Every structure is written in C-alpha cells, then in structure tokens.
Amino acid sequence: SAEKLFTPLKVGAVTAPNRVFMAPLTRLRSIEPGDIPTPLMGEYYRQRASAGLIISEATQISAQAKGYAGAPGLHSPEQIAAWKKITAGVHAEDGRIAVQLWHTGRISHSSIQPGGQAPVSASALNANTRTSLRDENGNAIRVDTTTPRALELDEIPGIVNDFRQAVANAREAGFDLVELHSAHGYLLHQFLSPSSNQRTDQYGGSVENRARLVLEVVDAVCNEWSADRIGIRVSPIGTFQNVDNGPNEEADALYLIEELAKRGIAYLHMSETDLAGGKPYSEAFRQKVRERFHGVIIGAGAYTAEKAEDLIGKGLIDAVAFGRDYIANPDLVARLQKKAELNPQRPESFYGGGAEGYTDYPSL
Ligand SMILES: Cc1cc2nc3c(=O)[nH]c(=O)nc-3n(C[C@H](O)[C@H](O)[C@H](O)COP(=O)(O)O)c2cc1C
Image 1 (cartoon, rainbow, N blue to C red):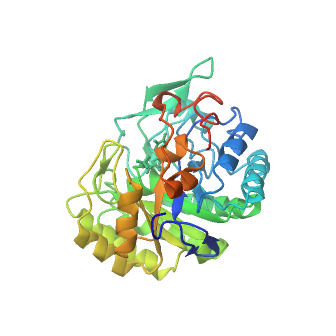
Image 2 (cartoon, rainbow, N blue to C red; image 1 turned 180 degrees about the horizontal axis):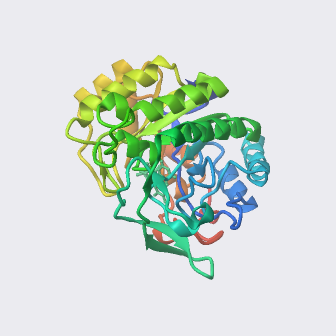
Image 3 (cartoon, helix red, strand yellow; image 1 turned 90 degrees about the vertical axis):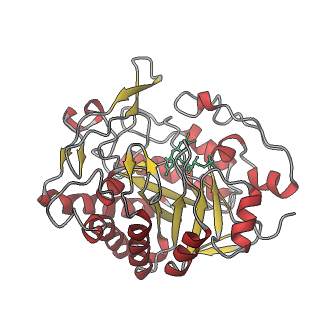
C-alpha cells in the first residue's frame, strides 16, 4: 500500500499518476545505419507505460553527439518518424514519456563520428575509459575512447543550436517532456567539471564559466518549447566515469541548481551515485538542494521503495527514478504497490542484443 509513492504529482506541463519513474536506460538496440528506434523498442516502452513517467534511454541531439553504437538519435527525419510511433504506443496505454537528450562528448570513438574524426569536448583530454561499439555481427563490444578535440569558441553556438533543434524535434515526436543529460561525464558535464574542463575562455575556470554552456542550453530549449516541458539530469556529487566534480562539488552544485530554478523548469533529476557506488548524500545537502529548487526533484541511484517513501515523506524529493528494477519489471508500479516479488535481473543483456533480456521480463 505504501503512502505517497502512489499519489499524483504535477511535473511541469504533465501530471504523473504516481511517483515511481522509469530512469533513462541505454540499451543499445537501435538500428544501424541511421541510429533508428525500432518496433521492439516501442514494445519495451509500451510494457512500462504504467510508470508515473518514463524517461527514455539517452538519445543523440545530432550525429556528432553519438558515442555508443546502438544508441538512438532524434535529429533525422527517420528517427523522428520512429519515435512518433514509440510515444504513441506509450500514450495508447495512458502513459507519459520524456526523451533524454545527450551529446556524449569525449565518451565516444572516431569510428562512429561523422567523417570518422575525433569526437569533441571541452578540452583535448581522453576520458581514459571505454564505450560500447558493435562488431561485424552486430554484437556489443567495449573499445577505448578516442582522444577528443577541444571545441573552438565559435563552435559553441552550434552545440547550443543542436540541443535547441533536438527539443523542437522531441516536441513533434510526441514526447511529453525533455530531459537534458548533464550528468555522468558526457558533454555538458565535461564542461561543468574542473577535471575535464581546462579551458581559458569564458567556458572554463570559475563555476560560473563551467556552468555557462549548460545554462545557455537550458535557456535555448525553454525558449524553443516551454520551461514546463524541460527537465535536467545532473550527477554533481562524486566521481562518474573518470569525471569528478572537483574540490568544491557541493558549493558548485548549489550554484547550478539555483541558476536552474530561475528558469522555472519542470524538474531537477539527481543521479546520486555511479553504479560503482559513492558517498551517500547528507541530509543537510538534500535540504540545501530542496530549498534552492522550487520544482519537482527526482532522486535516483540504488533506491528502494522504502528509501523513496522516506525521502518523499521528509519532503526532500518528489519522485524516484528506478533503473535496473524497471529493466526487469515492466509493471514495477503494480509490484511495489502490491509488495509483490520482483523478477531477477539479467545484466548480460542490459546492452545490445534483441528481445531476450529486453521484452521478455513478465508482468504479473
Ligand atoms: C543498463 C543501464 C543503462 C544506463 N544508461 C543511462 C542513460 O542512458 N542515461 C542516464 O542518465 N543514466 C543511465 N543509467 C543510469 C540509470 O538511469 C540509473 O541512474 C542507475 O541505474 C541507478 O539506479 P538503479 O539502482 O535504480 O538501477 C544506466 C544504467 C544502466 C543499469
């Protein structure tokens, strides 16, 4: 039965019937060439339409944004047409779906970049990690990331415009909301972090400069559509894919959050930890965040229904986004409400492949 996890929540322009959200989850099952969403993906999302809100897998705002083979885009006519079918399917089941838009920046490989050139970033520093590509048989594989090229100052407006255009495409595609991916070490986060950003122009140095790009993007997308259609995901505390938030992470996080609140966007999505773990958020920090962002706050990262109820009851967050539990349980809402057991997870099929480990997790 719980208490408040199953009560409606107004999220910007839409109203969620419950606070159990589906976190954005990269599954790398899109069609190549074209990075096109598939009917299988449409079925996967439709099965999970009872979620208070479905946040889609990270989706490219442009071809340059691509960093993983199999990840979908929302920049081409064919992609837009495919996503329209997916959102329609979710809506046919009375659900709501937001598209998470990203630019992977340095977490990419030249072989999947337009023209086969080096990927771009805030500075020319290799991520020193791996990304996922596909072999000749279409199977997912890990490959060391390519050293990026630092974006030139005159190239920045183009990046902002790519986000703006992607949001315009999202609107036509039928998405209820958009979530800017400003977390986990991808492009926006590469600029926010002092460890990945060594620029000496107005986009590097101070936190004001480091947050400049993401805020210009927020302003651009709010103008393109509406602030109440814009959400943003950040992971400002801890280290993510070799991208740490710096020696003043808490302070820098609060600066950004305060700036975001000024735009009156639909929501602030906090990814609290890397899958590898991280220091838990202090109740004091949660309080500081709460008071600086007057909109919906979504908490995520190894959450349990119990933890969600606790923090929601304390008025520190408004909803919770579950990732892996949603991969394995299409009807997670019903299971949590009924206290039913959950299907076991099969990590080996999280990335790539087909229907197995994707649409074959049964509902009650
Ligand atoms: C297979 C998989 C793919 C993910 N891809 C993304 C993604 O596309 N975008 C994102 O912001 N986080 C991504 N995440 C992080 C999840 O949104 C979520 O924050 C994380 O799984 C922790 O929550 P959980 O314990 O409920 O799974 C991914 C995690 C997993 C397990």
